[PDB]
Image (cartoon, coloured by chain):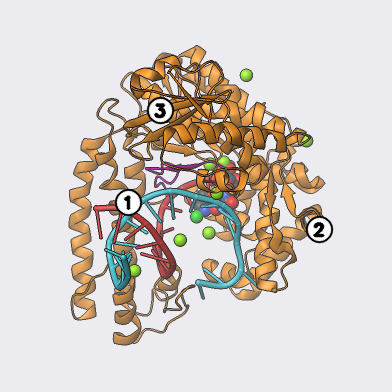
Chain colours: A orange, B red, C cyan
Amino acid sequence: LEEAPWPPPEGAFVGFVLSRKEPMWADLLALAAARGGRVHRAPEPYKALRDLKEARGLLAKDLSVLALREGLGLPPGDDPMLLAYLLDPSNTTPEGVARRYGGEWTEEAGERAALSERLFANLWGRLEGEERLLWLYREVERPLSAVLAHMEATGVRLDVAYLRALSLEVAEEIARLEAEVFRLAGHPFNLNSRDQLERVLFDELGLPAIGKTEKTGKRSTSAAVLEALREAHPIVEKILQYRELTKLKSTYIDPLPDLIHPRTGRLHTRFNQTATATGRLSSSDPNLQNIPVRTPLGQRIRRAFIAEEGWLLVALDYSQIELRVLAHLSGDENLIRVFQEGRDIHTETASWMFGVPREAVDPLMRRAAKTINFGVLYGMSAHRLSQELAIPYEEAQAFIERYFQSFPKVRAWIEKTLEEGRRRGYVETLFGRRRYVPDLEARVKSVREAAERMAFNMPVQGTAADLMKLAMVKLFPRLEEMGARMLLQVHDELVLEAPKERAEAVARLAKEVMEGVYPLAVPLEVEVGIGEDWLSAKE
DNA sequence: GACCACGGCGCC
DNA sequence: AAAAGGCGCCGTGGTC
Ligand SMILES: NCCCC#Cc1cn([C@H]2C[C@H](O)[C@@H](COP(=O)(O)OP(=O)(O)OP(=O)(O)O)O2)c(=O)[nH]c1=O
Ligand SMILES: [Cl-]
Ligand SMILES: [Mg+2]
Ligand SMILES: [Mg+2]
Ligand SMILES: [Mg+2]
Ligand SMILES: [Mg+2]
Ligand SMILES: [Mg+2]
Ligand SMILES: [Mg+2]
Ligand SMILES: [Mg+2]
Ligand SMILES: [Mg+2]
């Protein structure tokens, strides 16, 4: 392309190079733009940003977040990555997308600008006639990228001092556990090494091996294996506790306080829009979609996520969402009726599991039942089921039989979905998001059946994903108008931050928007909590 | 120093 | 571990 002076005309595609992948932490090393057979290279990248009306091109959101960081209201526009992702969600990297749709991802801004331009042209052409994918792009993905940019640049507050204090207490407990483990082993070793631990458990103490690892076929020391061996030797329970504590310390307690951004004094994640096979978002650098909540220490960590002073967190979470979605997709009367009657399948399963009335079910019981309900729905084996429930194999089988016998049309929907997946080569969500699954026609049964579970899950999980995205796009402008902030999405949950005086009003509005987003054959219900911290917000 | 596969595990 | 699906990050062992 003919080189030309900065700035570019309106509608130009941008290319840019960052010192690191995370836009909140990156230095903008170079910036260029391409349009109408011209390439414009910016002599001063930061200053040049103010000349742009929007960020249009590959990874548009990243440039937008950096702009927002610098106090510039630069929104993201067209991004070929989003087009490619909609065509085929295995399109997840600019490297792959460039190669596939007409170019090469290099480390030069001008070349990236030019690449963005021609990729958009090509990919736009491919989405012609694809009216549903086009709808998703214009009505969901493109606007959502703006929403996500603001969320990333906003960040969330973290009680750093608290976490620092927590680290020392956890360190002392870890020392206590490991010392005990070493005594029981008769000698010290690296307890963080599963290879060393395998030798101690199965060769030195005698313990019977139960399972093997996938790629290298070592004797597994996973929690599932250790659970089965809890009553075989005292060292086992000690290892399980050590694992729990060290996992939380190494992954959350220690890293997170070090990631507070110096300017904002908050913690900033990345919400990746083209990262999953089903249409879910992912979160990275750091991942804020897997903050602990199940165990006591886990809850203490979640409490470190706090509202700004004078503000409150609002947490909203769709109730039994994939089950409701399944009701709609399958059209099963029995399942639809369950939700019309305001029933809770997680609580009911829980009451059965622990053998107590539905009123006796506590949160941890219900949560346990959640794993069981979705586990069974998406093809869990009776053997695994029996093992995790410590009930005979025969009982496990029976629960799985009643589960489906309760809801006749679910299996019917599955069969139809798989048949159609085999025919077209892909499956799709309610809104037409696609996932290609060639292995539905695999000649190896284990490979084929794995593919089948992926395939019939995707329309359900993906539809739920689409609904949340649509809800975020509708909700965002309403929140702006109320002076509230959208902070995090956790799959079927949103976390907002609102001034205390308005927090209740914001909660009510957000709930109604989420419930009214796209009516199904069953009501959508959203549970909402308000609190000074994320854990308190979830009640 | 950086990458990698792996086993493992946090969340949904 | 086992016929749940979907993610990203940890330390280890290893290479470069
Ligand atoms: N398993 C740990 C407990 C939390 C969980 C979960 C899981 C959630 N999911 C999917 C199905 C579920 O509808 C969706 C959102 O999860 P979540 O909000 O925790 O469950 P759901 O909304 O069904 O129940 P509630 O929100 O508690 O009413 O994510 C699974 O497929 N497997 C799961 O294990
Ligand atoms: Cl889980
Ligand atoms: Mg790719
Ligand atoms: Mg939910
Ligand atoms: Mg609205
Ligand atoms: Mg949830
Ligand atoms: Mg419909
Ligand atoms: Mg892995
Ligand atoms: Mg699982
Ligand atoms: Mg290892």
Disc nearest the viewer among 1 and 3: 3
Q: Amino acid at mark 2?
A: Glu
Dot 1 corresponds to which residue? A251
Q: Is residue A516 visible?
A: yes
Q: Sequence order check: which comes first, mark 2 or mark 1?
A: 1
Q: Amino acid at mark 1?
A: Thr
Q: Are marks 1 and 3 in contact (CB under 8 Å)?
A: no
Dot 3 corresponds to which residue? A31
Task: Tell me which secondary structure the magenta stretch mostly adopts.
Answer: loop
Dot 2 corresponds to which residue? A419
| Chain of the residue under the numbered disc 1 shown in the image | A
Residue A406 painted magenta: no
Q: Amino acid at mark 3?
A: Leu
The percent coordinates of residue A371 (x first, y second) are 56, 55
Alpha-carbon span between mark 1 and mark 3: 35 Å
Relative vertical location of residue A190 with respect to residue A466 in this rendering, above or below: below
Disc nearest the viewer among 2 and 1: 2
Alpha-carbon span between mark 2 and mark 1: 42 Å
State which image quarter holds ligand 5: top right
Give the residue displayed 28% in from the left and 47% down from the top.
A253
The percent coordinates of residue A251 (x first, y second) are 32, 51
Q: Which residues are magenta?
A: A279-293
For residue A216, side relative to residue A440 (left or right): left
